[PDB]
Each structure stands twice: as C-alpha cells, then as structure tokens.
Amino acid sequence: TATFHRCAKDPWRLPGTYVVVLKEETHLSQSERTARRLQAQAARRGYLTKILHVFHGLLPGFLVKMSGDLLELALKLPHVDYIEEDSSVFAQ
C-alpha cells in the first residue's frame, strides 16, 4: 500500500534523509511510536538512524536520516502513507 517517491531532477535529490508521511488521522503519539519502531528495527540490522523531526499540525510523520537500504522495512511500518526522499528548493 505505502509508496516511495524521490525528486525527478537528479541533481536536486538529497539521498540519506527521508520524510515518512503517515495516514491522515495518525496521532502524534502514534507518529512518535512509529519513529521509535523504525529506529529499533534498523538497530537490530546494524543501522544507525536519527529522527531529526516529528511532524504534527499539518501532516503526521517524521524526518529521518538513515540509509536508503531501510526503505523496504520503513514502507512496512504501521500507519505509513508514503515516504519521500528529501530534495532541494531554490530562491526564484
């Protein structure tokens, strides 16, 4: 069900940082528990992860610095809607 997305403009992609977007009515407490679950599952596989930010107010989810190797595992987490690789924006 959950899908993955990355910027179509290759020079503007920022691999290694992902926005994990949870389903619309996901509560902040569920977002935090999901982020900790990802960190625990990643740690068991020998990967270091860092939760940079937990989102609430507009979209539920979190920002994670982690290897892209963990994306298949992250897409399987409860409440996940989609995951987007971070990318650049520029002054116009």
Image (spheres, rainbow, N blue to C red):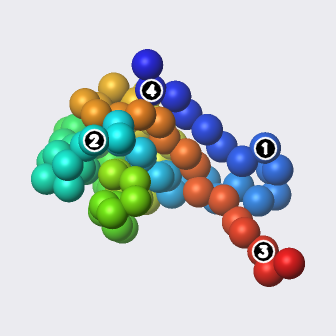
Q: Look at label 1 and name its amino acid.
A: Ala
Label 2 or label 3, whichever lies nearer to me, is 2
Residue located beneath label 3 in the image: 90
Decide if residue 23 is in sight here: yes
Label 3 packing within 10 angstroms: few (<14), some (14-19), many (20+): few
Q: Are marks 2 and 4 in contact (CB under 8 Å)?
A: no
Label 1 packing within 10 angstroms: few (<14), some (14-19), many (20+): few
Q: Look at label 4 and name its amino acid.
A: Ala
Where 16 falls versus 90 (above or below)?
Answer: above
Q: Quick check: 2 left or right of 30?
A: right
Task: Name the residue located 33 percent from the left edge and 63 percent from the top edge.
Answer: 57
What is the secondary structure assignment of the residue under circle 3? loop
Q: Look at label 3 and name its amino acid.
A: Phe
Q: Quick check: 79 left or right of 36?
A: right
Residue at far bottom of view: 91
The numbered mark, 2 or 3, whose residue comes first in the sequence reads 2
Q: Are marks 4 and 1 in contact (CB under 8 Å)?
A: no
Residue located beneath label 2 in the image: 25
